[PDB]
Image (cartoon, coloured by chain):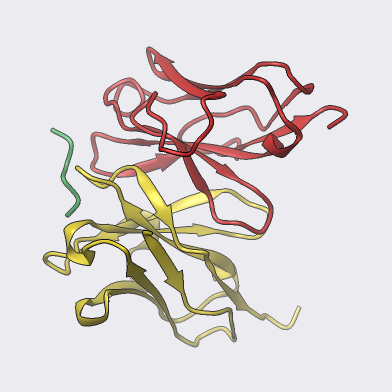
Amino acid sequence: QVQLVQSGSELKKPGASVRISCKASGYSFTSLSMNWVRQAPGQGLEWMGWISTKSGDPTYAQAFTGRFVFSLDTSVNTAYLQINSLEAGDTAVYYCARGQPPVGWTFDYWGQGTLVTVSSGG
Amino acid sequence: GSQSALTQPPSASGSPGQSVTISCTGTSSDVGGYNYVSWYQQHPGSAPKLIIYEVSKRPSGVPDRFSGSKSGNTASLTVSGLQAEDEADYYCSSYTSSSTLVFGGGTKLTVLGG
Amino acid sequence: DVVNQN
């Protein structure tokens, strides 16, 4: 079946980087886009942007421009999200979500989520 | 949630077996402009699950108790025959003419006496 | 008019 399996939880301090993976199986990886969605604990879903698995080119939502990087390793069917210069407010579950054909704006299959926790000391 | 691009009521309620409808208000540049409105169901600790796409289509395996429609700039999800397991958060989304996706703020659906 | 993401 189609499955998106993400890497495990992360616990980081402000200023650090983290790279999260999303490994796709059960369909041709480069045939469909990948979207990224963030959800802070207790809060709603936020669209971060998408990456084309044909070109590798990422398009970021306005709120996610600068510190966030979408990338791929197509040889292992994997999409990655890196967050640089982590801040306390980056604590969230990050989901990869497949762009359903034809255009990718319906998210038909979701990864299980990766919790990134940034500890501030208080 | 109340400041989201698409507006959903923060909460909704029904009783077992009842039908309930929840709305998702956008603009003519998104819900009212295109037929790429989706609804996602999310249980605690789980990823969102697609339940309605392209306004009214249902993925295989999703019960026909879930249905979607829109009128003007407002999309609506209806859950008929409410079951205890339908208690969850529901999010709408839409494509926009800016080549973005917007989300609603989510509705917590409670099943009274579930 | 809808952008094809991929």
Colour in which the image shows chain A: yellow
Q: Position of residue B86 (x, y in %)?
A: 68, 35
Quarter of image, res A33: bottom left
Residue B61 higher or lower than B46, as above or below: above
Q: Is residue A63 left or right of residue B66?
A: left
**Left or right: residue A110 compared with residue B106:** left
Quadrant in the rendering for residue C4: top left
Residue A96 appears at what percent x and percent y? 41, 62
Q: How many numbered discs?
A: 0
Could you tell me which quadrant the C terminus of chain B lies in?
Answer: top right
- Whole-percent x and y of residue B14? 75, 22
Q: Quadrant of the N terminus of chain B?
A: top right
Give chain C's shade.
Answer: green
Residue at figure coordinates x 19%, y 42% from the top left:
A102
Picture coordinates of residue B61, whole percent (x, y): 47, 39
Which chain's colour is red? B
Residue at horizontal 59 percent and vertical 86 percent from the top: A13
Q: Is residue A59 visible?
A: no
In front here: A100 or A47?
A: A100
As drawn, the residue found furthest toward the top would be: B71
Instruction: Looking at this view, name the residue that lies furthest to the right.
Output: B113
Give me the residue at 49% from left, 22% from top: B67
Residue B62 drawn above or below residue A53 = above
Toward which corner of the image does residue B34 lie, by quadrant? Answer: top left
